[PDB]
Length: 216
Length: 216
Ligand SMILES: O=C(CO)[C@H](O)[C@@H](O)COP(=O)(O)O
Ligand SMILES: O=C(CO)[C@H](O)[C@@H](O)COP(=O)(O)O
Ligand SMILES: [Mn+2]
Ligand SMILES: [Mn+2]
Ligand SMILES: [Mn+2]
Ligand SMILES: [Mn+2]
Ligand SMILES: [Mn+2]
Ligand SMILES: [Mn+2]
View 1 (tube, protein in one colour):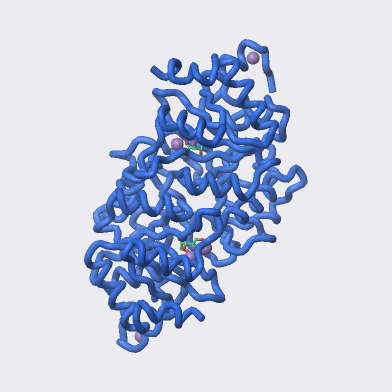
View 2: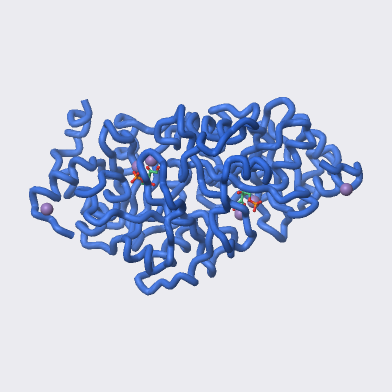
């Protein structure tokens, strides 16, 4: 079973603390959602320490639809409307219009360019004119309340950043197997060991956030 | 120089004929745009022969923002508005709202699911309700006139399909190097040799289309 597989990484509280510490150190983590939701694991990085090398890893090992988790306030500051008025996708992932930095990029799609775009968008001083639309970076609006309101990787990302004491902006993308199938827990665990990334679940985060009276 | 590098693949007319034949056979090709435009090479596949294995290759070797080139008529049939009213991106790539099949997929992001979504969308009998929005497939509207009107990989794709006698729907995605940089001509040539894919340029196509009085 899943929790038995993850025991390696420690019990739920340890799995959360280790993830937060990795983020504080500028490393990435792997977040699994509920087995009866997507049963998918996303690579998560903090934006403020994001490197080209981390983005290149995300592009070659994940779906390549690298998303930028933003707060509602930041998405509003950037004047980023939802991509679709009536989102009728299964999970209602809160995709905004896609974005590209106006300055400092070429075609927008290289690892370096995506990082430039992401840092431009996450800048607390950012203005809407800093971003062209559409582009190769896919911002998302996190629900107020984080994983205590919606148990998606989007909310996982913002909560991890806030709980680690970091700026509330992160990047995420679904870990994909070489044959195009999506990674499941055994592959995610092995990837985490290979790349020295902690693994944790949304459930771990919800338990942690509820037990430590953590309002963010 | 570039044309010297591509001489291996034949002269421009041969490069076009070989690409068309590969597509007719159900294989992929590599299309370079102008050196003073993106100077990027995209993998291109015909939709009607698209396999999970071809999509998996695109995801692991390219940007992972796998696009679906549609005619304006097909995009209209699907009720796919442009993602942004005033596209202010550099190349004005005609991204529609992103899509996911309503039926036959799980999370939409696996290689198989993206193919399911693409075939659902490309179906000449498709209806708007067949697709949820947003999703993990990124349709584009090709300009009327193809590469004789706009010299983008979008138009390259639709023109290759029409000239090969295939349904005018293809998938495309930018070839990316392992370190996250974008592949340039030497890397594209080597990739084409490895995967037995023909390489050609948009210029090749424009010359071919103008000399063979090819109205599509
Ligand atoms: O699932 C995804 C997209 O389909 C990715 O993990 C990310 O974009 C967050 O989305 P979320 O898990 O919150 O729905
Ligand atoms: O460049 C791209 C996106 O940035 C891709 O090749 C494709 O989506 C077609 O776009 P195009 O080359 O026609 O602008
Ligand atoms: Mn481009
Ligand atoms: Mn997810
Ligand atoms: Mn609480
Ligand atoms: Mn998803
Ligand atoms: Mn292109
Ligand atoms: Mn003509």
